[PDB]
Image 1 (tube, rainbow, N blue to C red):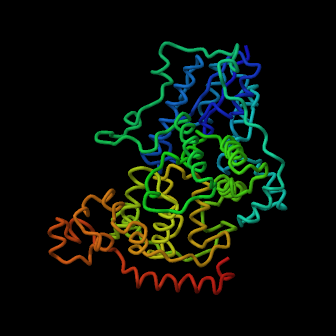
Image 2 (image 1 turned 30 degrees about the vertical axis):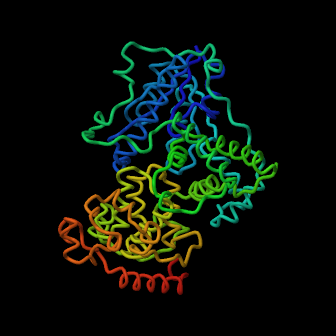
Amino acid sequence: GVNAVHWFRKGLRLHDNPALKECIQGADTIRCVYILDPWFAGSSNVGINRWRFLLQCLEDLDANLRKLNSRLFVIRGQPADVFPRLFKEWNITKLSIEYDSEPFGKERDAAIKKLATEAGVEVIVRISHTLYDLDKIIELNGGQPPLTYKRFQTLVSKMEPLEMPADTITSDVIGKCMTPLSDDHDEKYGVPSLEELGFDTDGLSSAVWPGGETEALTRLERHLERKAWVANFERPRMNANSLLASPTGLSPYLRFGCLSCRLFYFKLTDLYKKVKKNSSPPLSLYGQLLWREFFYTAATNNPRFDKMEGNPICVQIPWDKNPEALAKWAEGRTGFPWIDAIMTQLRQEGWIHHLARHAVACFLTRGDLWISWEEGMKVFEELLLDADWSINAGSWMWLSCSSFFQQFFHCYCPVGFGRRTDPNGDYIRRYLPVLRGFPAKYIYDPWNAPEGIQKVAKCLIGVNYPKPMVNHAEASRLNIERMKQIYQQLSRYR
């Protein structure tokens, strides 16, 4: 019969999946596949929390497919290796994917599309990771993506209204389409565990950010209620509680496709109309989505978007190379408790607040260590659940004054910012247990504590907790000057 395969990469959901919906139509069998390669050299920089989040998305998908009399098929290897075999073994005639705007993904998908054509397989591609056809936004701007958010906003408002989300894949939608299943499915196609990827899990705490569509859809409602409670759709002022992972947080779910950006858009729209009594919302309502769309648009036609050299939009700043200073930053042993707490939260949980990101990124790059944004990007890629190629590269260039016309950022103080955010130091004591004995007077600068205070705290600076790795006052003075000199002669660095 007509045997269809839908290939999950992002778009890890059954709601608003136009590619899956179209593939099922007119099909006699359907098999949803995810191609997992945990040992791939290109994925050697993926950390354990990202693996766990992915696996939990896959377990969620498999569970929801069970309800529809189907299963997720997890295939190990590379797509170019496995898809020729699958086409023959399953007699496939249709293959669907959600479109991938990222340069490497466009190259991969063009190769699979050629393999599918060679084997007599129809390919269905549908845009749903982003709100818009990014190529149309670029054409509206004259052929190049915009590099300012205000310009991007102007372009977005000129696009045609969003189409309605695709119907959720239910049993009624699946209809006559069935999924052939084997008694040994779990053994041959099951979702692997962390231990099957080679990871120890002994003593590992439960995920602060559980993966999956089901979780994403619950959080969507919490997110909307919080904005309804305050009748304000702008992003809120950060306080110390904002540093903690929130049950309203959506960013990892948008990154993996657990939550449709278009569903988020219409839910926001309907809530604004009800609360504000206005059919015409401001574009600020969609801020989180449009900043995301902005960096996707800037990245799609730039294969060196994640590099400095050979990147047409990036200022060529002479960053220092310092592997040992970089490692102290990445491992949260800088000796500045505010910085180490943030880097520890990041490593332990996979998410940190936007201003916390500014803080640690300023320290690494333009503020204290003068290390390339490319290196902070790589660490965030390993640890940050909501980091993807486009967002991660774009944000690291933004904050390092390397692109997007960004210049005189505030130079964050690795002591004063934390003290002003959380004067009592609860955030420090939560993520840095060894410092719990320090009073608030010294919690952000423990090297200033008298010896008697350190001894009572059972934490000797230089032994139980590191000395500060730099003199922030001198280092920031020199780096502020270096960045001033670069922008005094900016064209010299194009």
